[PDB]
Image (cartoon, rainbow, N blue to C red):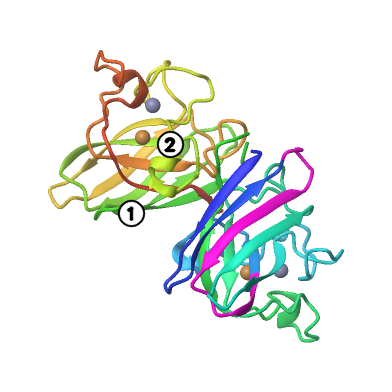
């Protein structure tokens, strides 16, 4: 895509929104926004390999590094793709970010879509610490906050054989959903657990944008690259993102087990860097006879969502 976004959150007070824009498909990426809750001074700022936040920032794995090079600073030949250097927080604990980088992309095998942006406790020494740790992390220390990099309203995306989504919302609904596609236009297995739901049927869809800047609202409509009407997963007439219903048991738990051949974890129907949403009400699978049925299945409000990240 030509635009991406990341909401950074952690166990402490660090939070922010970082925007990405890439106008020419392998030109430089503009990176800008704001992070607050930081100590005054320099903080390591990196793309890590996996958009897996199922164990906070730890499950993001190491720096994104397809080239197997040593850690470096940005404007520097020997670096990781994900080495974006340092952000500087002012005396109000705010880092105003304004970067331009040519090594990261929002498309291709060097795409950061569906990966994790991390802000660190300490400064990145940019590989010039002498020791071994410096040539892997820049001695940047703890991961204070992170988020999965999602597709924002523009354009695209990213590529993997496993993906994962951490669902959260305003209310008590939360869960983790796993995606596995062992052959690269075969079915995607979709499995996991969501809790805090009312007993019964809940609409379950991939929405177009991996944008959670305004909660689930900013995820936009159902992912619909073929411009079809909403349907059930078994219908010819459906959105790519229309995975049907999941069922919550009397304890409010939906043990999701789905297999879909229309979604993909690569190519132009890739759901990497898009948002998975679970809904208030049953999806009528486009059989409701009203205009809303043909758009959303009358599934109602978005109880929880998250950005679908590369796991594999
Ligand atoms: Cu990092
Ligand atoms: Cu939906
Ligand atoms: Zn690095
Ligand atoms: Zn739909």
Q: Residue at x 56, y 49 (%)?
A: 5
For image coordinates 26% across by 15% down, the residue present is 290
Image coordinates for residue 138, horizontal then vertical, percent = 71, 77
Residue 17 visible: yes
For the point 64% across and 55% down, the residue is 32
Please, is residue 297 above or below residue 63 in the view? above
Q: Residue furthest left?
A: 250
Image spot of residue 1 (x, y percent): 64, 38
The magenta stretch is 23-44
Is 26 contained in the magenta span? yes
Q: Give the residue pinned by disc 1.
A: 175
Dividing the picture into quadrants, the one containing residue 230 is top left
Rate crowding at label 1 as few (under 14), some (14 to 19) or many (20 or more) other CA atoms within 10 Å: many
Residue 225 vertical placement versus 127 (above, below)? above
Q: Does 24 appear in magenta?
A: yes
Numbered mark located on residue 279 in the image: none
User: Is label 2's Cβ within 8 Å of ligand 2?
Assistant: yes
Which one is earlier in the sequence, the residue at label 2 or at label 1? 1
Decide: few, some or many residues near mark 2? Use Cα within 10 Å; few <14, some 14-19, many ≥20. Answer: many
Cα separation between marks 2 and 1: 15 Å
Return the residue nearer the eye: 291 or 80: 291
Q: Which residue is mark 2?
A: 206
**Residue 303: image x %, image y %?**
29, 45
Q: Residue at 53% across / 75% down in the picture?
A: 92
Res. 61 visible in picture: no
- Helix, strand or loop at disc 2? strand
Question: Please, what secondary structure does the residue beneath circle 1 have?
Answer: strand
């Amino acid at each position: 895509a030509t635009k991406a976004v990341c909401v950074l959150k952690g166990d402490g007070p660090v939070q922010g929104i970082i925007n990405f824009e890439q106008k020419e498909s392998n030109g430089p990426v503009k990176v800008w926004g704001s992070i607050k809750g930081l100590t005054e001074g320099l903080h390591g700022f990196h793309v890590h390999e996996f958009g897996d936040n199922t164990a906070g920032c730890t499950s993001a794995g190491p720096h994104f590094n397809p080239l197997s090079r040593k850690h470096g600073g940005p404007k520097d030949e020997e670096r990781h793709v994900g080495s974006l250097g340092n952000v500087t927080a002012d005396k109000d604990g705010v880092a105003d970010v304004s970067i331009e980088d040519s090594v990261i992309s929002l498309s291709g095998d060097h795409s950061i879509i569906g990966r994790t942006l991390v802000v660190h406790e300490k400064a990145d020494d940019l590989g010039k610490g002498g020791n071994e740790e410096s040539t892997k992390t820049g001695n940047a220390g703890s991961r204070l906050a992170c988020g999965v990099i999602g597709i924002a309203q523009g354009a695209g995306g990213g590529s993997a054989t496993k993906a994962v989504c951490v669902l959260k919302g305003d209310g008590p609904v939360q869960g983790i959903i796993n995606f596995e596609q062992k052959e690269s236009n075969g079915p995607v297995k979709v499995w996991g657990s969501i809790k805090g739901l009312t007993e019964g049927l809940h609409g379950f869809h991939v929405h177009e944008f991996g944008d959670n800047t305004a909660g689930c609202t900013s995820a936009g409509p159902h992912f619909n690259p073929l411009s079809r009407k909403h349907g059930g997963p078994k219908d010819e007439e459906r959105h790519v993102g229309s995975l049907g219903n999941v069922t919550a048991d009397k304890d409010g738990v939906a043990d999701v087990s789905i297999e879909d051949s229309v979604i993909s974890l690569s190519g132009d129907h890739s759901i990497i860097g898009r948002t998975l949403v679970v809904h208030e009400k049953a999806d009528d699978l486009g059989k409701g006879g009203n205009e809303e049925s043909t758009k959303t299945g009358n599934a109602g409000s978005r109880l929880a969502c998250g950005v679908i990240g590369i796991a594999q």
